Figure: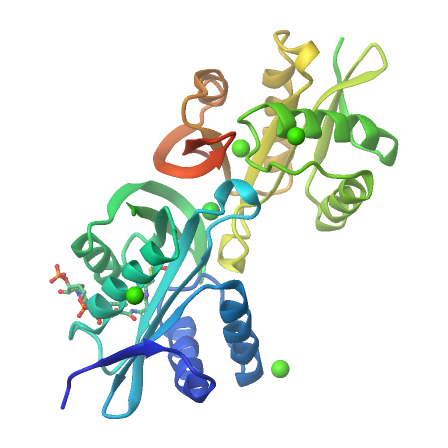
Length: 165
Length: 163
Ligand SMILES: CC(=O)SCCNC(=O)CCNC(=O)[C@H](O)C(C)(C)COP(=O)(O)OP(=O)(O)OC[C@H]1O[C@@H](n2cnc3c(N)ncnc32)[C@H](O)[C@@H]1OP(=O)(O)O
Ligand SMILES: [Ca+2]
Ligand SMILES: [Ca+2]
Ligand SMILES: [Ca+2]
Ligand SMILES: [Ca+2]
Ligand SMILES: [Cl-]
């Protein structure tokens, strides 16, 4: 069965989450640094998420985690406390099949429940999948910061999208 | 005669008072809680260790404003991008202090090989927006209702200048 179970992340999910995360760093422009992490790193990340009351959702298919989404602080200090910047990652062999849409729709509902006012996505301008994903859930384009990032001697642009809850 | 120079430890009390005045009273900084001197001490020390300038404008021997920049975002991908702030003392407003600080800070940024400067401005602040525009900043876009202060929502406009 391809049907997904959507639920909160447990420590048992960490190896899956680690592999999805490291693959996204190394192979995509989803994260603008090249830093690979380890299991202990993600363990701390998860603990700090739970402690801070930020959710981490996973999509599970045939017993295997095939994607996850979370959000955290957009910018430091009180002024921005009701704005959160989100993350979503689908396993590299499972993309284009609606897992992303499912995870984002649910994360949006969690954020509403937890009184988030604005969800923010910072997206590389050429990330067509992410742009389509967010547009499908009612995110609107705010604008683009040109050449603010860099890969491999190549300047990247950052598009912001937002959804007021 | 405004003198523009690098900040010292001696300047921290004046820097603290201008920073806390903005926090306490205006929409220019979206923190609510004031900071202490040790906090500004650590801030300045990290600025200097990281090679990010802190410039002060001095007139008749007193600090009447300052400007600095720092990381726009944490990811090393953004290392060549810096977000800047310019602060003028409220009793010293309207005399070219903002324009002069911003101009020298731009020179310091090129000198240090910054690629892009970013300003995050409260979107209704037409004066701050004009000031940045007059030095070649272009509007990127507005994040609506992303801030809150004093019981109201605030919109953040990003402007940029590629150096
Ligand atoms: C929020 C940020 O910080 S941006 C970073 C986002 N995350 C990443 O980039 C990590 C790497 N990529 C991924 O993990 C995934 O590609 C995601 C999360 C972006 C999308 O998840 P998926 O499960 O592939 O998305 P899903 O199948 O639900 O499709 C989402 C939309 O993107 C479109 N799409 C999916 N993949 C692609 C692609 N490779 N090229 C073009 N369009 C695509 C779909 O057609 C769909 O559009 P529609 O709603 O208009 O029909
Ligand atoms: Ca380790
Ligand atoms: Ca719910
Ligand atoms: Ca007060
Ligand atoms: Ca600002
Ligand atoms: Cl940001």
